[PDB]
Image: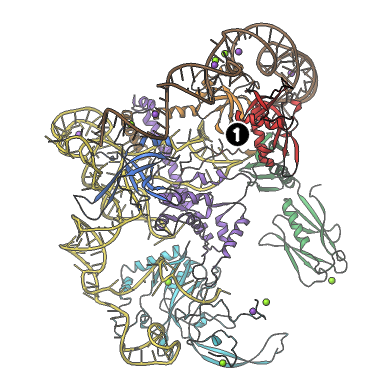
Chain colours: A blue, B green, C red, D purple, E cyan, F orange, G brown, H yellow
Amino acid sequence: PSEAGHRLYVKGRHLSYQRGRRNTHPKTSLIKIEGVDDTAAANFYLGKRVAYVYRAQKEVRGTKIRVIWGKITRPHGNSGVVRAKFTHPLPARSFGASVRIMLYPSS
Amino acid sequence: MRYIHSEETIPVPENLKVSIKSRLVTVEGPRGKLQKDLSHIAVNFSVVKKGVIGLEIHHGSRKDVAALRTVRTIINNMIIGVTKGFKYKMRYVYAHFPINVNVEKNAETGCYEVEIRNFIGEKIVRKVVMAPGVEVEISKAQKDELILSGNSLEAVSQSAADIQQICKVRNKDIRKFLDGIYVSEKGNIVE
Amino acid sequence: GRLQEYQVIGRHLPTEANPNPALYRMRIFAPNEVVAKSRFWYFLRGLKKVKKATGEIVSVNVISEKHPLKVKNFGIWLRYDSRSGTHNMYKEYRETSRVAAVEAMYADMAARHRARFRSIHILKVVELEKTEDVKRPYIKQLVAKNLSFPLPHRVPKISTKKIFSAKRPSTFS
Amino acid sequence: SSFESVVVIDGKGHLLGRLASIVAKQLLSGQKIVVVRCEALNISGEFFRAKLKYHAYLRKMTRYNPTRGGPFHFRAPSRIFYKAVRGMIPHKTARGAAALERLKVFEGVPPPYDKKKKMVVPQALRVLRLQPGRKYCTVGRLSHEVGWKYQDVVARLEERRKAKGAAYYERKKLAARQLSEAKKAAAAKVDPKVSEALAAYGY
Amino acid sequence: SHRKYEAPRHGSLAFLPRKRAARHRGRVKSFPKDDPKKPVHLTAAMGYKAGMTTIVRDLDRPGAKAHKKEVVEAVTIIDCPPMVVVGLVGYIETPRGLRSLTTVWAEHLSDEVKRRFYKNWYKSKKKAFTKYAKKYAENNGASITRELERIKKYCTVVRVLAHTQIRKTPLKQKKAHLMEIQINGGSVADKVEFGRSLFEKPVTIDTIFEKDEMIDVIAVTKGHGFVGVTARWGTKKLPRKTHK
Amino acid sequence: AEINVEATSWRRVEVGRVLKLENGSLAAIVEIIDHKRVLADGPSSDPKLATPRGIVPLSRALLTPIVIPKLPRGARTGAVKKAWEAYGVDAKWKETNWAKKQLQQERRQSLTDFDRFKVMRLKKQRRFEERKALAKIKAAA
RNA sequence: GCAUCGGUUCUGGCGGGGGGAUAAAGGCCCAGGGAAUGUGGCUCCUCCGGGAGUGUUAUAGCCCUGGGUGUAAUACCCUCG
RNA sequence: GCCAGAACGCGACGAUACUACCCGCACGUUGUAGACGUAUAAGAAUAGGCUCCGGCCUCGUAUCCUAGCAGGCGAUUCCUCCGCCGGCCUCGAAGUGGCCGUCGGUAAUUCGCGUAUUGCAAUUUAGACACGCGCGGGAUCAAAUCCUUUGCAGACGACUUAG
Ligand SMILES: [K+]
Ligand SMILES: [K+]
Ligand SMILES: [K+]
Ligand SMILES: [K+]
Ligand SMILES: [K+]
Ligand SMILES: [K+]
Ligand SMILES: [Mg+2]
Ligand SMILES: [Mg+2]
Ligand SMILES: [Mg+2]
Ligand SMILES: [Mg+2]
Ligand SMILES: [Mg+2]
Ligand SMILES: [Mg+2]
Ligand SMILES: [Mg+2]
């Protein structure tokens, strides 16, 4: 019975902040989206919502899981990387962790 | 300056067969089998006619093209040796001390061995091992003569050079002391 | 699309002792018309006693290739400067337009003789009408009869973003 | 691009430096890598040039005490490759240390990683990068000549595992031959119109 | 500037860490390389040092000055009661070196060996191999023969375990010494057959070595304490009027 | 004399060879410029297979197994068009495996969400018959 | 969170107008002139695939010079939405 | 060959009291550089290869799997696919796979009942390893240090010995 999964988002990875060679700006992050490899493909995802979910120690209001919400703003480079802004900047220990790219604001 | 097309040809007698596979050449004839590996050269083989082999190099540099004639001669010698064979001769040269040579055929390895004694009156004894497939023999037509024969020109020539290079005079004027064993004639077993 | 051939006509300013001065015409290869005019005064300064402050430009026109679909052989005469002394050369090219021939020449001189754009004078560009007028052996092999050749060891084109192939690529395309 | 749980790379025929830079970037992104057959890697240029390079490396050592601080010269083929990767990573940071924890390197193919799929990095393959006529060497030969002791042990073990693979390949060929026969017999059995609908869809 | 006159350095850097040895018993770091065409045999033994004495013999060395004349030479005496074989070990080749995968013992062990596994033997319960011995009486010792078959199939180096009978010497010590001795010989099956047939049997030194043979001796040297540079390395003494 | 040679056999660039370009178009070679460039044109009636007259770099082309016989060197567009249609280049190109692969790829990319559901269900019905047949032959060994 | 707006900015697509040799080419048609990396024929050498002569459209075609369709199309530069 | 032996490198073996050990079940008072279909084993050449021997190769742009209350309860219908156990073989590079049997589940076809109200979005609290706790069953009855002693050892610790 129903040997299928339940996935409605696209996978992504947190790479780093916006930076120069020796200066870094945490207010913006760079995200790699799986499967997109050029600027034209990345134009589809402008404006979507991004979620970063993780675990904590204690329960607050019925759970031990927390979220930080954000959105995609503009492309980056020539190879499909994009920029994003979150409500709070990401913790920077998560360089290499995974995020969820929604489809909420559609067409 | 690259050359678009360079080509050479090789005729083949009706008494033998040739096989090429992944640039590995096998020549089969009335006197034995020979093999050669040419996987370090970018060349194209083909069958031009009923009994002619073709060699091609496309878009080659001046340095690259120089190796086309080299490959042709090597394979051609392989055909000649398998159908006629090679034969080198050496001669003893001495002034005062005679040179004594003894030749024995080893049993475990099937090779030939050559021993040299009394070179400029030295007490040490010199020993050289011939390459497999090369046969040595003391001459009976004339004195102080060695005869080396075989199918591979590379094998016969390198073995003959081993004998010549082992006998040297040290700390003397070699324009005056001319003793040694030297190659004097190169030819074929047949004809 | 880097160069075009222009026609430039110039003149000395008319004076009372010489109304109606003579007119001079040159053919200039340049990326645009602003540097076409600057190149004109450079060459004329070396031949006649005229300057830009004592002359004026009469006309500028673009010369287009008459048959940019026919394969041609070209010959070029030039003069250039090395690190010590100046020399004359003659080279040959095979393409479909005069503009294409000059662009190939500029790349060729930079590669083989380290000559910059600022140290080359073009003397003459001529289309060779007869197949007997070909002199250089690297052109002669291209005008041979019944030409044909294969292409061995061709690397297939693979997207950069696709790392981690699951099979060994071939080179027999 | 694709996210995997682990990627296993067959090291035969890859150029040492180019494979090293690609592997380093994957680790910093958050991908786990395993490299096998490190003895079959390649280096461009003649062998004699590679030997002179290592000898210059060997001459460097701490003067006042050779047991501390000094460059420690590892000899195994997998440790030569590991050194090249570590130079392209900020290994003195906590982030850099975590990245190196996602990599494994081996000589030969140890039992965990046979019976598994091995990929290839075409941006670093020798037959696709090097101009024909140039010269190259193998890391396995360089290691043998600077003091690596287990070249023949690995050579004998590799022969055994290839002999087992020949038996496995024989079974795999039989299965394909039967599956093709089953599809032929079942095709003309039943499907009256499913065949044409699938063909129109491209399947 | 350069040193005024030349002189070699004092001492050798090959024996460099001048520290106390890790173990009291000597350690065999290599064995003679194996030849499968020779009969199976042992390659080492152990004994105790008694002292030195003097002998007289006539030399045989053509061309020498003392040819066919008597000479005086010093010798050393080693006390060697027989050894008892207790078990064997197997080894395999890996890309990381040799490692041992099995070892199988004998059914009965003497109190000499069992003292080696203890540091307070006088107040222990002495249960060292009590449960292992029962493996010989279960299923006709199928577990014992299973391990022997494993060595025949995978291993390529076989060694034996042997200990001294220290009660036959005038020493006050009661705890024996134990070591591994490699077997060089025909085949791996032959090595196991030979090694197991020697279980809890004495082996005499005359079956291992013979007369007019060159051998090597491994041991730990005599100990001095904290020593200064003059005696430890052999440096020149400084003048008589040197302060400090 | 016995000679057994096993080596490569490439397709040659020549006057009359038909090339395939990046965007599925076709062209015929009329003149060779260098070892890297060629003058070509394709006068095809099908708007998806036609290309203008011009120079093509050989690095962006593939050699098809089709060669127009006796195409004069340097022939103009009118002469090429006549020989193109007389030989039947369009019909020959449709029978190659390269064309069929392209057609299959186009069909799969044009599937909607409802089509994807139906192709899953249709494959299962064919798969059911496959497993029954495979079990029968394998059981009989 | 969504909808309708204001300020700034990044990025896609579509419809027109003007210029130059009133683009240059090019397809089709008319008239004249040439040759060769010489098509078909004719001759000789090999049947062993072919090669060598001869000469100007034939059973292929190519290059120059004028004219018509034609205020043709398209590229490039500028410009109104 | 010869010296040292990583005090955060590894292997084999002996005996293991204190519920320290083994098995089964059920929980979370917990941790993890970061599950969400975490699905894919030939070797070799690249100026050559694969094969069912008919043929095939730019291209993983592939193949497998994929529907039902986060996936219910019945029927029609089918003999496919999946899993826990048990028995035989097999596996040594850092030990794995295959065959068989019982049992449990199961849209390839076609239907009948149920779904609402989480109120127009808010992580889809779902995996795998470790660790802790509580039961119910089995198995087991050990050593080390101080202390006295030795001198093959020694500044003191440490070391070779005996009780
Ligand atoms: K001094
Ligand atoms: K806009
Ligand atoms: K116009
Ligand atoms: K016209
Ligand atoms: K003719
Ligand atoms: K239902
Ligand atoms: Mg002298
Ligand atoms: Mg000095
Ligand atoms: Mg004093
Ligand atoms: Mg706005
Ligand atoms: Mg007009
Ligand atoms: Mg117009
Ligand atoms: Mg240690």
Of F50 and E140, the residue lying toward us: F50
Please report the residue visible at 46 percent of the width from the left and 27 percent of the height from the top.
Answer: F100
Q: Is residue E184 above or below residue G77?
A: below
Q: Quadrant of residue B107?
A: bottom right
The extreme front residue here reads C16
Of E242 and A65, the residue lying toward us: E242
Q: Is residue H6 above or below residue H157?
A: above
Please report the residue visible at 41 percent of the width from the left and 64 percent of the height from the top.
Answer: E150
Q: Is residue B16 above or below residue G17?
A: below
Ligand 5 within 8 Å of disc 1? The answer is: no
Quadrant the N terminus of chain E occupies = bottom right
Q: Secondary structure at mark 1?
A: loop
Q: Quadrant of residue C90?
A: top right
Residue F12 visible from this viewpoint = no
User: Residue H37: x, y in percent?
Assistant: 32, 43
**Residue type highlighted by circle 1:** Trp
Q: How many marks?
A: 1
User: Residue B174: x, y in percent?
Assistant: 84, 65
Q: Which residue is mark 1?
A: F10
Provide the chain ID for the residue under circle 1.
F
Please report the residue visible at 56 percent of the width from the left and 65 percent of the height from the top.
Answer: D60
